[PDB]
Image (cartoon, rainbow over all chains, first blue to last red; front, side, top):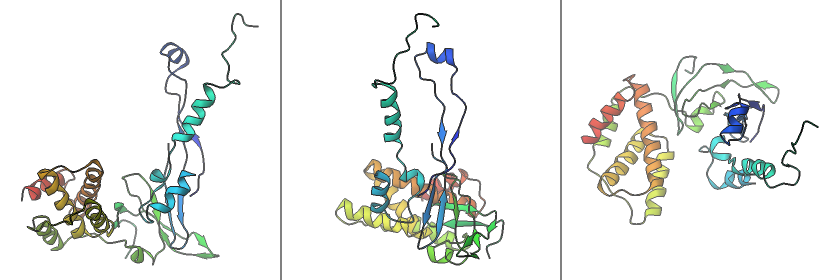
Length: 49
Length: 49
Length: 159
């Protein structure tokens, strides 16, 4: 199993709204995983949150 | 650790990265760093200095 | 037979398209990898040009096997072993076999036992997955309007 290429989305809520609504200020993270079968030969590339 | 554990138990040809990957310890590690640590402190604001 | 534009069926990932033939280098040689685009989890599966039939990449179905799996779905036979563990193992093996008639047997047994008793959340997830792969297979096979594929599934479940 292999990971590659981290990539961020946009922030889900701005700073003053996050400070007012008592919610953390974050952004989602995406990692392109890849699962390789050695003897048979397959690659299952996906996208994981 | 749990990826290489559950990689061998359930069979080949049925596994995918989204069934291999469990993001709960990663997100709990980030949350338990940002809360309840002595290096992530409350910001000391009485004034700009 | 595998050119660009097919609709082939993987063993237990569902029916998928093809869009390219990759000549990706392995051992200094360009083995003809063919790519897949299966839309249940948007994963791309790339397989060598000759081991696809070994792993069970099965072509689409458009003949009297449709009537065969219809009479398999509307068959009178319903028998399972006494213990739920062996019953689940046998149904999981028939699901992982990747055959349309066997998947039809799995969904008719699970749907009969769920409309009679109601078993479990794990077998509910199993029935949802097998119904998803059967509905998607026939809807991309006959090109017969998916979720009206679910209406004709309701028809053959009513039998």
